[PDB]
Image 1 (spheres, rainbow, N blue to C red):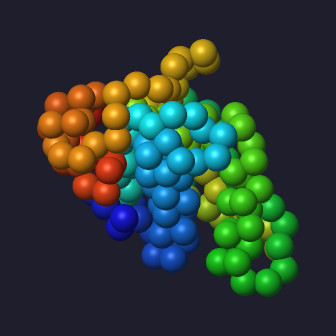
Image 2 (cartoon, rainbow, N blue to C red):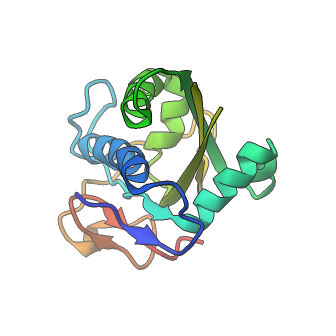
Length: 173
């Protein structure tokens, strides 16, 4: 599993922050696809999220102007917390707390989202938003299909490569 990056730029958040968030997202997704994430249900077709600098820039706009992303019909997650040590360790902890928020995790884990980007700001407290190309709806079922082994296993979107049992497309729009 490695980060798959598209666009620019947009990507102004530093690499390890971007990577920590991307790994948290796609790591979970990969485990869910293989039906082996405690509490997330049976194996399924899953798309990896492409990290998208354009959407990171939308996340930055969303921080400055709450409501921005919804206007562009995006999914949004937010996570924050006070901290004292290094930003990178705090983030890691904030993500653990974040992973216990069932409503946020619905977006994180939605098999038909295909790209996202995040941005944060420091004030010592940090605030992050993530913006996703696809927002699930309430009651929408997430189960279905199978974890990909080859390209032809990815059915949700046209031009998809299966990589680490995740489907990747760059043209879901």
